[PDB]
Image (cartoon, grey):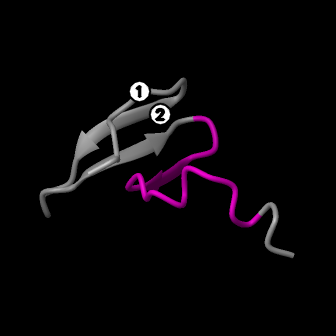
Amino acid sequence: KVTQSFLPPGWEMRIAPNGRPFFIDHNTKTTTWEDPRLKFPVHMRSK
């Protein structure tokens, strides 16, 4: 699919035992998988 693996500053790409790669941002302490829509601004437009 159109979901490419990239390594952005602060993020760390690892693999979860469930078989999905996850990105953990060491800046904001966040950890999630790269969702398609997550890559685009959703919360900062949905008001």
Percent position of residue 19, x then y:
12, 57
Amino acid at circle 1? Leu
36 versus 11 height, above or below? below
According to the picture, the residue beneath numbered tag 1 turns out to be 7
Q: Residue at point 69% right, 64% down?
A: 42
Residue 25 shown left or right of residue 6 in the figure: right
Discs 1, 2 touching: Cβ within 8 Å:
yes
Q: Which residue ends up furthest to the right in the rendered image? A: 47
Q: How many marks?
A: 2
Tell me the chief SS of the magenta region.
Answer: loop
Find numbered disc 1 in the image and state the secondary structure of the residue it sits on.
Answer: loop
Q: Nearer the viewer, residue 34 or 4?
A: 4
Q: Residue at point 45% right, 57% down?
A: 36
Q: Residues within 10 Å of mark 1 (few under 14, many from 20)?
A: few
Q: Residue at point 87% right, 76% down?
A: 47
Percent position of residue 44, x then y:
80, 61
34 versus 42 height, above or below? above
Q: Which residues are magenta?
A: 27-43
Q: Residues within 10 Å of mark 2 (few under 14, many from 20)?
A: some
According to the picture, the residue beneath numbered tag 2 turns out to be 11
